[PDB]
Amino acid sequence: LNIQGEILCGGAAADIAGRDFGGMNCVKPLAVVRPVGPEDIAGAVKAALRSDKLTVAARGNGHSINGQAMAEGGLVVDMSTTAENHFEVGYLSGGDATAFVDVSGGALWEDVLKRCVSEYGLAPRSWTDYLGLTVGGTLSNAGVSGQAFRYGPQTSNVTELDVVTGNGDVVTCSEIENSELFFSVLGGLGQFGIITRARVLLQPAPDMVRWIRVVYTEFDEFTQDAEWLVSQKNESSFDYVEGFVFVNGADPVNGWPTVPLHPDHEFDPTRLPQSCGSVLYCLELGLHYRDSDSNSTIDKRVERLIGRLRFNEGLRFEVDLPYVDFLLRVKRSEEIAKENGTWETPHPWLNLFVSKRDIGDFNRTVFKELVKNGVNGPMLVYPLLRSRWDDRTSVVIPEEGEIFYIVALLRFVPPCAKVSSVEKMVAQNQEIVHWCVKNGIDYKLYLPHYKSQEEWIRHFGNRWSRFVDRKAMFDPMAILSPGQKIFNRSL
Ligand SMILES: Cc1cc2nc3c(=O)[nH]c(=O)nc-3n(C[C@H](O)[C@H](O)[C@H](O)COP(=O)(O)OP(=O)(O)OC[C@H]3O[C@@H](n4cnc5c(N)ncnc54)[C@H](O)[C@@H]3O)c2cc1C
């Protein structure tokens, strides 16, 4: 290995690369690599290829839950040291997106957002909720948030990547050049190569955002309205659709206090009808607009667009704050988080896609019964449109329906809870997964984590052969991101 950066063994370095946000694994590698670029990364890969047991896993921000970015006794590539390696904007006359910003696979989304807006007036159009995540990390899964119904997830918003494959080759790919690789890497859980650069689409950045949260007590009403809103003609309705499932109680972390947006308007439960479940549903909406716009004009447009929603009057919270605060709103929960001690404890989260034909059986038992007291955080569930997603990528979504729902229990661990707590949480996630498999629920996990081949073959379904062909082509010794646990390293 010939590297310009600094390698670290043991101590705090190995310690950190041995932990993640989920807090359930501490797998130590032989070393941590700091690549000053693609060659240092290819060096790491090739060392593993000649070696007897070393593997190779790129790390982004560590946000993962189950150790997918770890390499027991192998190499971890600290992509963090390649973050500022790219920032080149170009225009697209091809209609659709305006420009692009070739950015490093190691760049963080929040920093990208700031620089892009604080010097150019352009922004990517498809995001994730949390921005303290890397470009390569989210592009290796899908990158989903509230703009995906309109623009697809982040993997649908890249037009070129530089990748260091499991063969050690440093390559640039797109739909045209080295295409099978391009599509393999997108959503491919780090299995076919490390993403050092991505060509991320940019649209003109909006000025402002009207942030809305309204409340429903009836699911099929909340779900019918949500589907109706995301099914509207492009740019005729909102620019953000979200929402969750909170408990029908005062629990400041699981209940109605988690709904309002600003401190001067709180949730008055005396507006809820007597015949509502132990849980209510919030619909979360975001409308983009320019600061030159007259408030009376904007107010009239919002009423127009919300005029056909069946929520409950008197339980529709809203605020108008700048596009950038609206996008870093997750920093608001990261704060309460640290203030309450759980931002630091284990997070045995649950994330999944449950197609429309099956989301119904989910609110029935899961939300209203299994986790009716909440999981100590948000419980999202917004609809999406399969049409926006390209089946050429390595991504995996439900088998049937032009509309599927993204799911995700944002489980936290109160500082009090015994360690037995995290076991019951994991156990309950496994149970939900069991309940879905046993009832033939067409669900698939997002950020999937399985420990057996038979679970991975089922998850990939008819695309398992393709996932195997791509592996045999781009990482035949199976040295890449072995922590995903889909393929075992070569003997
Ligand atoms: C509270 C909370 C909220 C969340 N909200 C969202 C959300 O709104 N949207 C969303 O999409 N996700 C969300 N997630 C999941 C989260 O996005 C991921 O764990 C996180 O983005 C991982 O990102 P990372 O950048 O740290 O990379 P990693 O955790 O390191 O994960 C990416 C996988 O890719 C590999 N990898 C890392 N960098 C590269 C690279 N450059 N090239 C190739 N492979 C690489 C890793 O080894 C790993 O196997 C949330 C998680 C939590 C705990």
Image (tube, rainbow, N blue to C red):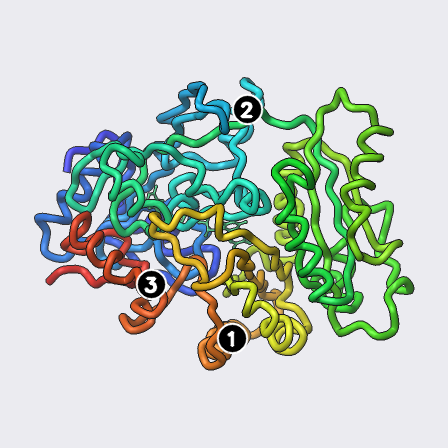
Q: Which residue is mark 3?
A: 460
What secondary structure is found at the residue carrying circle 3? helix
Q: Amino acid at mark 3?
A: Phe
Up/down of 44 relative to 462, above or below: above
Name the quadrant of the C terminus: bottom left
Nearer the observer, 326 or 76: 326
Work out whether 101 lies above or below 220.
above
> Label 1 amino acid?
Ile
- Where does residue 166 sit, x and y in percent of width and height? 19, 46
In the picture of the structure, the residue carrying the numbered disc 2 is: 122
Give the mark nearest the N terminus, 2 or 1: 2
Closest to the observer, 24 or 300: 300
Task: Identify which residue is drawn at 80% across, 65% down.
Answer: 250
Taking the spot 46% from the left edge, 81% from the top edge, the residue there is: 438
Find residue 26 and report its horizontal and vertical position in percent. 36, 61
Q: Nearer the viewer, mark 3 or mark 1?
A: 3
Name the residue carrying label 1.
432
Quick check: can you spot residue 84?
A: yes
